[PDB]
Image (spheres, rainbow, N blue to C red):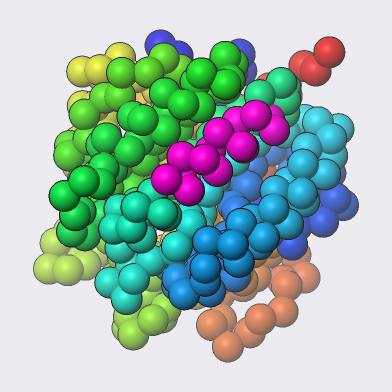
């Protein structure tokens, strides 16, 4: 089974676009993470200035984002970290329904392929880059005649990247949203060195409680959306992903998973523990969402939605992540 790295497991986190060199060195050398997902994100997700920007404005933004990623790679090497390059905001962004314009517009669809050829050329020889996550949480909506849907665009883009780059994993999330259930909708891509990826936030009423218009006070384990949720329910959520893994003989990467920090009592920590245990049973690489990004997802911030101060002492959730990072092997660079 192709993984694209020679370690037992990648365990790390999403970082924020403003992550400092000191943050990276601390995360690798002190927290013992061996992995980050580097999001090429224009301000926010799922809504961004990309949604209304011209292709020229978008290419200018992305060139700045790639310059910082390039500058960060030698720091990741020093920190013992392998990197996922995540195109988090694609050219044209998304319409009001969060559907990606790369599925709707000939110029944006062509730009997606041209951009990935440029990124593959830039990083083809990097021993720090692990994989190319072609688009974050793809959502198609209506695909006009003459344009590729995600199945076809993924395959074409992966083929063009593989022509340039003979080493790195190509990471493909299913549409819609990179959700576990969506993997059943994706056919394996006929390109070598492909890794498949989903994000784990199910159930959203729990993991995103007190975000958007979602009520707070949702306990885990417990009854959520009229259904019993515990580790067995999360196994059932992830069953289509385990099936895809086993039936296709492919590797799985969890690009994001989290539970909001202000979930009641130890609910968020239990959710993360249950997720990680399942990922570990199945041999899945994983990135926690997120290290030093929005504080709702921060293990350095506390249980109170109204308190945005870092905690004085380590949280349950931070101790859990570091206990798993302590199992990591660091990459050997030459």
| Residue at the outermost bottom position | 306
Q: As rendered, which of 181 and 307 lies closer to the eye?
A: 181
The answer to whether 311 is drawn above or below residue 120 in the figure is below
Magenta extent? 110-123
Q: Is residue 117 magenta?
A: yes
The kind of secondary structure the magenta stretch mainly shows is helix
Q: Is 243 displayed left or right of 210 in the figure?
A: left
User: Residue shown at 27%/35% (left/top)?
Assistant: 152
User: Residue shown at 77%/41% (left/top)?
Assistant: 70
The answer to whether 80 is drawn above or below residue 202 in the figure is above
Quarter of the view holding residue 30 = top right
Quarter of the view holding residue 229 = bottom left
Query: Percent x, y for residue 45?
Result: 48, 67
Query: Percent x, y for residue 51?
Result: 45, 71
| Residue at the outermost left position | 226
Q: As rendered, which of 231 and 7 lies closer to the eye?
A: 7
User: Residue shown at 21%/67% (left/top)?
Assistant: 224
Query: Percent x, y for residue 306?
Result: 58, 88
Query: Percent x, y for residue 22?
Result: 87, 52
User: Residue shown at 84%/39% (left/top)?
Assistant: 75
State the quadrant of the C terminus: top right
């Amino acid at each position: 089974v192709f993984k694209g790295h020679n370690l037992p497991r990648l365990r790390g986190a999403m970082i924020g676009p403003h992550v400092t060199n000191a943050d990276l060195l601390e995360f690798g050398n002190v927290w013992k993470a061996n992995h980050i997902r580097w999001q090429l994100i224009w301000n926010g997700f799922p809504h961004s200035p990309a949604d209304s920007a011209t292709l020229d404005e978008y290419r200018q933004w992305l060139d700045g984002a790639l310059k910082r990623l390039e500058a960060a790679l030698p720091v990741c090497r020093e920190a013992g970290i392998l990197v996922t390059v995540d195109l988090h905001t694609p050219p044209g962004g998304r319409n009001e329904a969060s559907e990606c314009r790369i599925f709707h517009d000939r110029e944006f669809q062509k730009a997606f392929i041209d951009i990935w050829e440029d990124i593959a050329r830039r990083f083809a020889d990097s021993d720090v880059v692990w994989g190319y996550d072609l688009v974050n949480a793809p959502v198609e909506g209506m695909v006009p005649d003459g344009l590729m849907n995600w199945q076809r665009l993924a395959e074409e883009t992966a083929r063009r990247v593989r022509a340039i780059d003979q080493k790195h994993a190509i990471i493909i999330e299913p549409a819609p949203w990179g959700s576990p259930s969506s993997i059943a909708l994706l056919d394996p891509i006929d390109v070598p060195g492909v890794v498949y990826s989903v994000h784990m936030y199910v159930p959203h009423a729990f993991t995103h409680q007190g975000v958007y218009d979602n009520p707070v006070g949702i306990v885990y384990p417990g009854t959520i959306d009229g259904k019993w949720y515990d580790r067995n329910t999360l196994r059932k959520v992830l069953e289509p992903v385990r099936r895809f893994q086993e039936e296709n003989g492919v590797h799985i990467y969890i690009g994001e998973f989290s539970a909001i920090r202000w979930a009641p009592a130890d609910s968020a920590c239990q959710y993360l523990k249950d997720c990680i245990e399942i990922f570990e049973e199945y041999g899945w690489d994983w990135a926690y969402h997120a290290f030093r990004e929005w504080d709702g997802w921060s293990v350095e911030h506390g249980p109170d939605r109204n308190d945005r101060n870092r905690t004085a002492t380590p949280t349950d959730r931070a101790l859990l992540l570091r206990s798993w990072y302590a199992e990591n092997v660091k990459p050997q660079f030459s």
